[PDB]
Image (cartoon, rainbow over all chains, first blue to last red; front, top):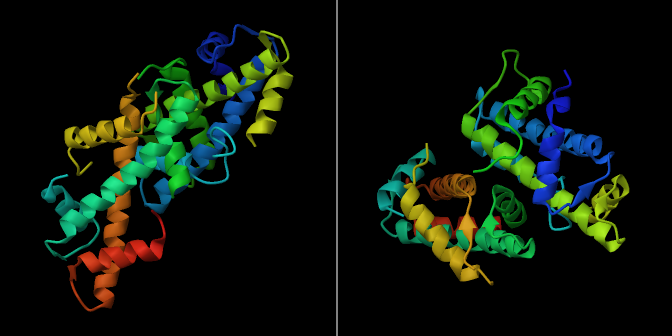
Length: 80
Length: 66
Length: 78
Length: 78
């Protein structure tokens, strides 16, 4: 259903402090929730396409690698 | 990289018979590939001021190389 | 290998999404190595974005990240 | 199933990464190593299949140095 709600506030803060954020305005959590949902939708869409093209029933790490590296998505910036 | 490993690799690839000259050639290829991908991975890591190479860096270097 | 979101919820979410996009009727399984790969990547991804966002707060003399910072970060990244 | 032995692969990764390291030597995340090796092998198998295609085109079942080279040259990759 809405398992994106299961991505926890302390988690996001924990991700933030790892990225050097001293403090967080309240609206960032939902925003961080949307970015991830959006992101794991491109990747999982692609991973699943590789698993089926290979006529397989398990998603493998090579599917995840290939999904991630696929064109038409920003990973870091202008480079890719 | 062992020659037996190149042999298994070749078979997955459908190859029936292998010239002895192919082995050194595959090493040159694997080394060249690892050079380009690792150069890009490392370059990004240092630019992010990070101290460890992540799967995201690899995936990013893969992206840009092929 | 040190994850910041707990394995259990992240896996739930991964199923939900894969259930919607897969072409198969029976639920698709994931190797445990694959979901950990994905999670490490997803976390690294949000950290990259969180730190760009942070840089844009500092640029504006704030220490508190704001929605608009994260939105400007996404504009400049492409 | 990875066909290249993990230890010798990891060796080569660390050497190369030391050669390109600019600043405090770099460490690899074990999931990152595995991803690279996973991609490295898939690259070689693909390249081995193309090589085989050029051998059959020349009516040979023995793959040869010159088949691999023409395959690389046509691809343009690297």
